[PDB]
Image 1: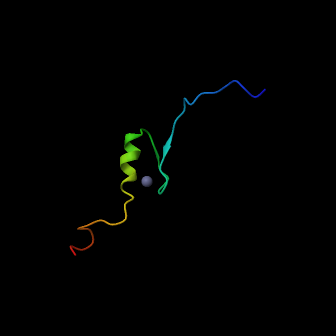
Image 2: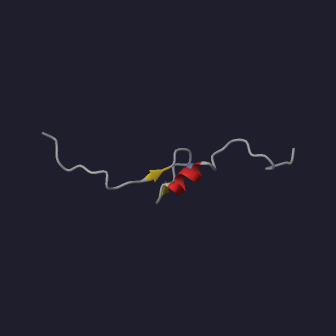
Image 3: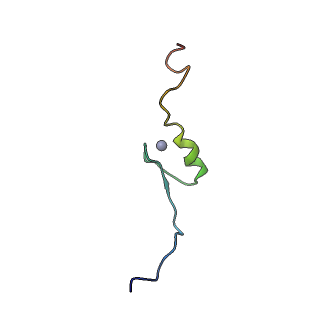
Length: 46
Ligand SMILES: [Zn+2]
């Protein structure tokens, strides 16, 4: 008899790598990108 109060009203989007809490979703999904090993034209041209 543990039924009753239930609702996914409160939502929180917390990254995985950095584990930073955000406000919206689109903000996170896109952010996650930042975590991509291998960036061309970064530290040195070649
Ligand atoms: Zn992150």
